[PDB]
Length: 70
Image (cartoon, rainbow, N blue to C red; front, side):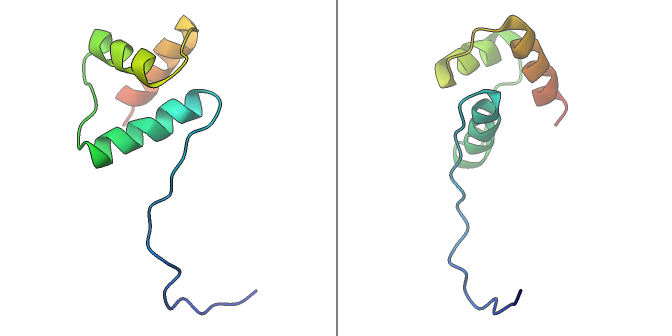
């Protein structure tokens, strides 16, 4: 394995999986491209159900704790 490290194009890295890892990738897109992400639970839940096919309340609170762990 070998290096050349002269250009390797520009960074951008688009991401969107089948499950809560899409929510995590789209949280990065909001806090980078939009600069901001919601900081209070009921507005953040509105945003999560706007950004994904979210239905599992146990995964919603697991994700809210993961978003507060930032």
